[PDB]
Amino acid sequence: MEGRLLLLETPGNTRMSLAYDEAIYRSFQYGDKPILRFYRHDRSVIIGYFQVAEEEVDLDYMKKNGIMLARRYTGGGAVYHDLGDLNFSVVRSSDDMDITSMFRTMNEAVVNSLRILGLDARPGELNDVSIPVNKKTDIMAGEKKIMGAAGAMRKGAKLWHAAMLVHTDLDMLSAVLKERVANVTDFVDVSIDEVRNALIRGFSETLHIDFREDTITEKEESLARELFDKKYSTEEWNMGL
Ligand SMILES: O=C(O)CCCC[C@@H]1CCSS1
Image 1 (cartoon, protein in one colour):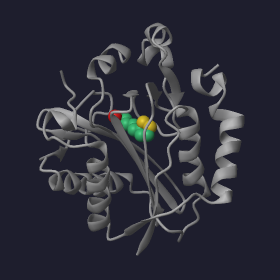
Image 2 (cartoon, helix red, strand yellow):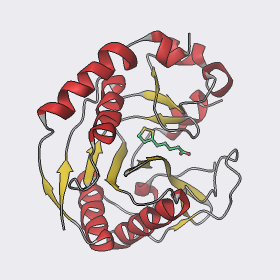
Image 3 (cartoon, protein in one colour):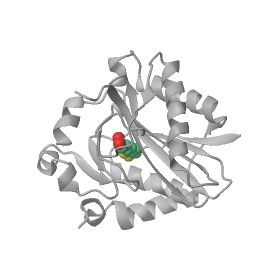
Image 4 (cartoon, protein in one colour):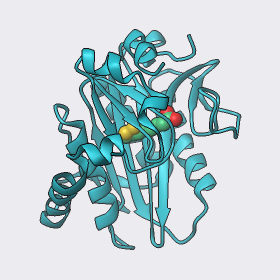
């Protein structure tokens, strides 16, 4: 089956990037071409939809250091991104609300992709959502987390997007979200492009979809702009004013 590969990234505006990402999710109609989107964000902390900013991050350190706060539309915990972090989102038709199985199948895809790069990894073991590593939504290179993910479902559509640490500043990560995380490049000598290419092939093989490069539609673009103008660009959305 043919998919859409969207190489669609606004690294200098994380809030707009997130607007793009709900936009593609919400524009999706059951039976549409499944979407695989790759993107990076400059220095940024992205918190879960339901999180209290000042409980989860050092907002004073962040402002002092020019790190953008951005709230995403999926739940889950807070993460630090920079240009060393590769993000990706998968939107597909859905006939059920079995989110566990979604994470399971996307993690298989990620594991297959990393195998291509010579890196052995598994999904974490634990259900406890509050713990920092080894969750079933994490991907673990042994004891170290190298990737986390969040997702959402509605009638007819699912979304699952993930942040992979390729060559992220792990010291900035630890400072802003206040030994357990690692970069992919701590294990194998690879570029972001090589990682992206492995993920394309791995997701294609695992999901049996051929993701061909495409652009966003006028409808997807206009919704993203609306979501940004009315929501993602605002302090109320991000800070929860
Ligand atoms: O590590 C976690 O537990 C949450 C991962 C959230 C991934 C999002 C991908 C696009 S924005 S941040």
